[PDB]
Amino acid sequence: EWQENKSWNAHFTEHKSQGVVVLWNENKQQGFTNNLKRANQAFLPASTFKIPNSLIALDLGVVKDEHQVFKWDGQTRDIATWNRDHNLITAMKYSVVPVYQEFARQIGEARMSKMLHAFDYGNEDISGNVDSFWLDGGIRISATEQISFLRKLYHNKLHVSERSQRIVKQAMLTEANGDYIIRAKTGYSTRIEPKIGWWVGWVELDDNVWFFAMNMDMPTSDGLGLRQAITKEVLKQEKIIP
Ligand SMILES: [Cl-]
Image (tube, rainbow, N blue to C red; front, side, top):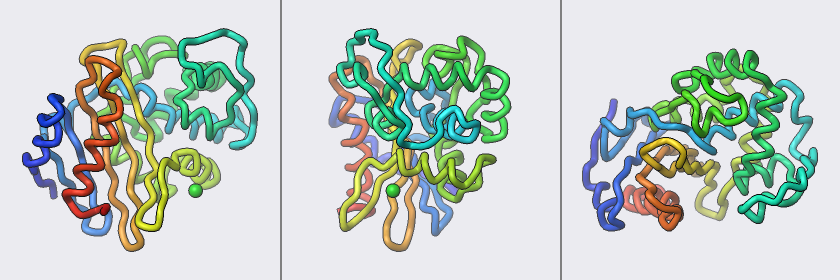
């Protein structure tokens, strides 16, 4: 069952933005969104693709473990945190595209395509360049589809090893305190209109898990912090976090 709560639209309009938050209550098997249509509209995954990409790279042995160092190629890029060595943890944390582009090249088109279908991931379409299709190729995924995929990951039900799933969930660790744990991944899609920001993941409580997926219009990078801020305002309104 699904419920539309348009009162959450206030959290977007108060920031002169537009978007969708989708929440899934795992215990109750109930979903909630401010916009049922946009919850089911398909967008480029951008850096949220680093979740499936990490899983595939680990399961195939392209990445041995979360400590393996991916050396900076020495090419100066405009994101300072990218001009350094990374492991899986820091590459996820800083959304280090060029590390994940090399993963995709080593995975290759055929194995990437087979694995996205096994994951039931989005439209499963890797049309485009193997090292950029999640940024400007044919792949698309909706917020509700993000939740379906994340629920499988949470339960270790994806068709990769338990180990690969545990490592990726470790790499998704974003926040933890005495009240909750958030495992999540941001995305920022600018190469194909409409430009959007993503935040997808889940909130672990003592006695429940709340999965979430949001995207929002992102005409400039000035608003990127709103991805987490709007999501958390919704979580606070629904008494999921303090
Ligand atoms: Cl952890």
